[PDB]
Image (tube, coloured by chain):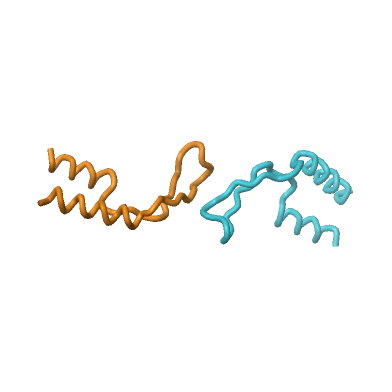
Chain colours: A cyan, B orange
Amino acid sequence: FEVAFLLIQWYIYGFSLSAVYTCKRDPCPHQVDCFLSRPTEKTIFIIFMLVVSLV
Amino acid sequence: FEVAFLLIQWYIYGFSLSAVYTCKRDPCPHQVDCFLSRPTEKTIFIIFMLVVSLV
């Protein structure tokens, strides 16, 4: 279960968060730029959880 | 002068106006959609002026 959850996280998200996300969805015309909330602190906590899971 | 102005109009604009214009300029992120004012009536008057110039 631990390795499966790690693989799913790697597939969907990776292990980092980018401040700017390019979104191409049906309602939005062409491509739009979106901005996440506190990407850096979330990335830090993501790395922390990855290390915890690995241990 | 008449033929030169007609050629310039053909090069820059053509002889029609589209309601939706796709704009890709530096300030705008990616591509944006813009909407002209009364495109159809302007197209009608453009054709009228083209006919007048041709005559």
Name the residue nearer the viewer: A14 or A25. Answer: A25
Tell me the residue at 65%/43% (across/down): A20
Side (left or right) of B38 relative to B2:
right
Question: Which image quadrant is residue A2 in?
Answer: bottom right
Number of numbered discs overlaid on the protein picture: 0
Relative to A30, B9 lies left or right:
left
Farthest residue to the left: give it.
B55
Quarter of the image where one finds residue A9? bottom right
Left of A14 or right of it: where is B41?
left
Give A53 or A13, whichever is nearer the viewer.
A13
Viewer-side residue, B9 vs A42: B9
Seen at 81% across and 44% down, the residue is A47
Q: Is residue A25 above or below residue A47?
A: below
Residue B33: x %, y % from top left: 47, 51
Image x and y of residue B51, in percent: 16, 53
The front one of B45 and B10 is: B45
Can you give x and y, in whole percent of width and height, for residue B44 in the image? Answer: 27, 56
Quadrant of the drawing holding the N terminus of chain A: bottom right
Q: Is residue B24 above or below residue A13?
A: above
Q: Position of residue A5 (x, y in %)?
A: 81, 59
Residue shown at 38%/54% (left/top)? B38
